Image 1 (cartoon, rainbow over the protein chains, first blue to last red):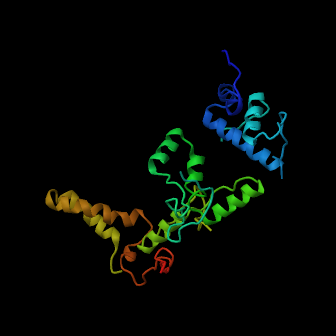
Image 2 (spheres, rainbow over the protein chains, first blue to last red):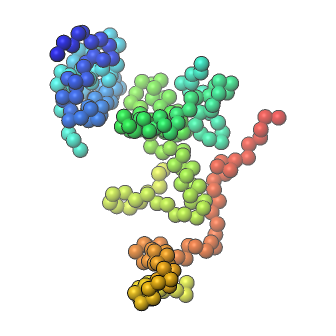
Length: 76
Length: 108
Length: 67
């Protein structure tokens, strides 16, 4: 209930992420593929959807975009 | 205290050495694999047991990919499996890995 | 080479059928090893080595030690 301002690598919260996928194991790949994409962007080749920070790591962008709900996944 | 990003490898085994004198790595045991699998972190373990240790193309390709700042290449062909395949074929056991459907292949 | 496998199989079947006891017991260990070659594609010809394979050079390496 009371989030109490989380910071850094615990942001964004894991519970708000877990809700998007079926299980955390899905969320891992669901993020990691978006991380793989934003990795590709610097060289789909979609850009950073949520506002990218000063030197934010690909992982954090993916998790922020999953927290923003800007992606969908397909259970193989 | 001991650290190793990369360094000088052994000739006999193709995994980093042990000890601070030879600038070795640090031993990733079975019990760590058990825990990785208990987490269910296939990618971490499969990264630890391929490019981080064995695969000669793997280590240089991942170093190259890291310094270039590109996607990490998917670790394909571990040295251990080549060793065990060649070693089993040395004891006159024909081992061929079949796909779900179609014809079989060599690893390279 | 001078061996038809299905004969040994069908003989084994009547041996385990009729010869119940010690001979069925000795036939029981034979059943698997014999019946393998019918259900499997590989022949029993590969048990005898005309050619012997050689493990790669680097798995049995000759490198000079310090000194």
